[PDB]
Length: 127
Image (cartoon, rainbow, N blue to C red; front, side, top):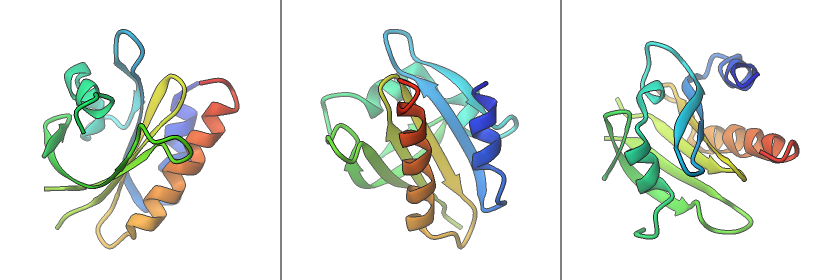
């Protein structure tokens, strides 16, 4: 029930988009918010995110990388901004990418916190 995690991420009303995306072997969106951006994330875009070469695009949306610690052990998260702009945080679990976009005026620190904590939750189930 991957949509449950999307629903919880979208519950407080301060996030406008969220997604859980598998990146092993054949990247694909496992769950996202319909009619938004992250539902259109391509495997090619995922490849950029988890690649060795470290703007970028997420489902067509041009983004600017603020802080990249995604492949970094202990953190595994990346903060971006849509090129009114919105804070974006991507966090890497054992098999997925958790993506979170905040609404206007929402702190990047909050989006990072929510995404980071949601990813820790997923890792507890070995995902």
